[PDB]
Image (cartoon, rainbow over the protein chains, first blue to last red):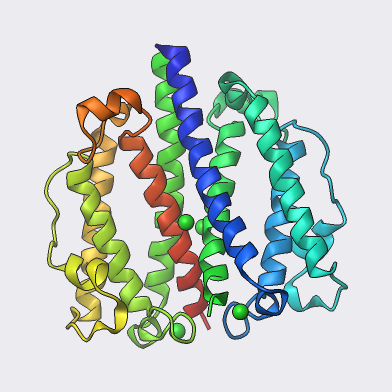
Amino acid sequence: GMHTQEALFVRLALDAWNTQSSRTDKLIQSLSNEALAVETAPGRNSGTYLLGHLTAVHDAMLPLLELGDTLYPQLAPVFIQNPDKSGLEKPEINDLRLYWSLVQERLANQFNQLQPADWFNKHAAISREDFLKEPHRNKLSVLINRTNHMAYHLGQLAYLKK
Amino acid sequence: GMHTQEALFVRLALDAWNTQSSRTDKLIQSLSNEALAVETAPGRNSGTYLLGHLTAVHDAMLPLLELGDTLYPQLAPVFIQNPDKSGLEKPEINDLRLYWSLVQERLANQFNQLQPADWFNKHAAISREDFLKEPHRNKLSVLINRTNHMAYHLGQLAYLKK
Ligand SMILES: [Cl-]
Ligand SMILES: [Cl-]
Ligand SMILES: [Cl-]
Ligand SMILES: [Cl-]
């Protein structure tokens, strides 16, 4: 019944995250460093930047979902707070590939241990008071939102496959 | 309790559809016909093609979700079954803009009348027998999937804004 239904909608949301994650991971693995460094389209973000961006955004989900601290806080100034052509030094690409992999794996670990119910609790960026009015502003809503963020950028990364 | 929880996860899924739909619609409205006709990136699909593609894919959700027949079946051969540079004649762009708008509005109408429970029934492309094993293969799973499909293509349409 109701406990089972809650488990089914967590499955749906997690299956979409996992599908986008698989596609993103496989795409990144398929590209050489030289191919990743190219702009996704003229004047637009490089694959390297999008990799770092996705990594930083996913890492930030850890504290937002009360699943632990970020692993790599120094990525956020480079890949969230500043644009690609900022002139700020980036990590080497193979280090970014590893950070991506370790953030994704930590999230998978943590997600796989959460009970369906925990997903319906508030995320860290909303007050208890505001969550009462809008209980849809929960941890699952973050998962859903970031899954679409990833899909959006995956459409751009797709243009690096020549 | 459980009826309320079911309503909250429909809200979450529909809010994501509506957010992507808003962003897509506003982007399309912001582009001139000449700007939409340009390739999203060198050698890649035009905005026109992606508009027709999104329209056809969304129209196909009507029968899949048992919400009525497709409005514009002739779009599917042009924008789903064949690629952009097929040489097949396309509708005029302003006709495509209208088809997009009418499909989106029909879907909104229909979605706004469905009860949360109806979203947890099977979609038209799975058997009752197979749905018993995998009840997550429901109407909501289609909504979620097509929301990420739209986000993916929205990332590409974004590159038409010069
Ligand atoms: Cl995808
Ligand atoms: Cl490339
Ligand atoms: Cl978006
Ligand atoms: Cl353009």
